[PDB]
Every structure is written in structure tokens, then in C-alpha cells.
Image (tube, rainbow, N blue to C red):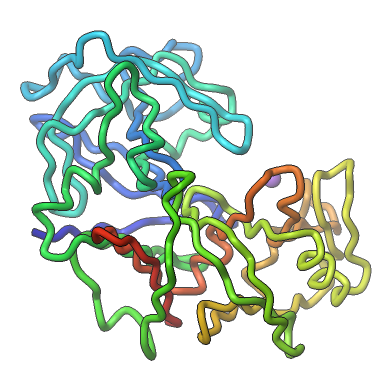
Length: 330
Ligand code: NA
């Protein structure tokens, strides 16, 4: 089997991407944030505290003929941005892009933090990291990918995120028309439960490539590119008037600037992030200070290749017995 679903930016900055997901019988379609940096599939629901729901579409298990309470199971998760959610668990039928899993754990939110309530466009998350990070207790649950895997034509999914445009998540096949050149595969460590890999270095603009190992994760649920402070300072030093602002919470730059590209290494291959991808616009409405898309990872404890980096590539998440990542230009 295979599945193919379009993923759409939630706003004009590509802050996140939503993908429609069918849950239950008859189908209830919710727009989920597919997150390769977490392992829970959780949704706004008929159980979510009413004051914490503001425009989201909810899952109502009582209206699904295939829903069953997973008795005694609870979940609670905290993300890198300080947001959180928690609740109870149902099993139900879940379909993505025509690929169906029966008996998927659907984690129903009783509580969500303010950042979730305030984002009316995101109805929940669908985690695609390794199932060792799933928060369900006392019986840990599998991701949608892990449950689908054995049915898939190939044990893979691909992320093809757009810049200011829709893109695609495919399950079970490589679309050889969706990229240019060849795919370069690189080793993955699953020790921390993430799609963790080592980039071979970077360049700023037309500058020379610096060969240096950068361990980090491929995370579709993170908007920005978080890298070591040395790398990030080297980038922003090429932008006149750029500075790190403790008041704003990262590097800002004059909105009048033209940003340089950023290149990262994948083995002997190179992925180029155009400068435009690194502009996240005014810090507040009407400001002439713009927020940068490359930020320091210092204090986060891991480097994160988030959407700024991933949307410059066709990315293969190879879930074979020995997992690997693949990157191609597009
Ligand atoms: Na922000």
C-alpha cells in the first residue's frame, strides 16, 4: 500500500504545515501538524476543556462506530517551545492520503496549552519520530508510520515541504519526479528517538564550504533552523545590521536587507537554502526589524533541521531495519 497527502502552510510565513487526516467511521477529517520530532498522534476532541478550544475542528469518538476507549491509558507531552497537551486515548481507524491503519492510538486532548488554543488552524499533531518517544502510559503506543510500515510497498515516508506553497507527504514510495539529481543517504541514530543525523558542514552565501560535523535532528514540526552559535554568528555577520536581541529572543535583521543563502552538507552533497527562506518578516506588525530563520541552538541541547532547512530538499525518512535519511535537491 501507499498514501499521498498534500501539506499546506498555515500562514504566509510557513510557520507550520497542516495535512488532512481522516479519523473514525464515518470519517472525521482533522488538519494535523505532521511532526518528525515527536511520536504522539493527538487531537482536539469533544473531551477538550471548552475554554481551550477556539476554532479547531474536534474529534468526537462517540460519533465513530470504530472508536474504542483504550482503557486506563493516558498521555502528556511537552514540546521544545514550552507548549503541552494531555488526555486519554482511543483506538480508531486513521487514514492519510488513502493509506489506512486500523487500531491506531488517537490521543484525545483534555487539556492543551495556550499556544495550541490560539492556533485555530491546527487540530492536533501526528508524530513521525520513533515510537520509543510516545508518551502513552502505561502501555506505550506506535506511531501511524510504525503501524503502517509492514503494509507499505517500501518502509519509507517522504517530506516535500513548499516555500510559501503546498507540498506533499508520501508513504510507502519515492516519487522520482519530485526531486532533481540523486538522493544522498546518511546514517541515523535512534538513540534519542529522533531522526538524528550528522551534517558534513556549511557555507554562507557564496563563501567557502566549512567541513565540520553537525549532529542534529530532521524535525518537520519545528519552523526554524537551529544550529551552533559559531555557525549562526558566521551567517548573520554577513547581513549588515543583524544582531542577536535578548528582548526579541534571537537574531533580527533590517527588513531592508537581502539575505544570503545557507548551504548544509549531506555526505558529499550540498543542500542550498535560498536567502528568502530565512526571512520570517517583521517582529511585530509594521516593524522594520525582521526575525531570522536561522537561530542558535545553544540552551536547547540539540541542533534542529526544521522546516527552513527541510523545505529546501526532498527528504526521505527510511524506516528500514537500519534507518537512514535521504536528501535531494528539488
Ligand atoms: Na515567533
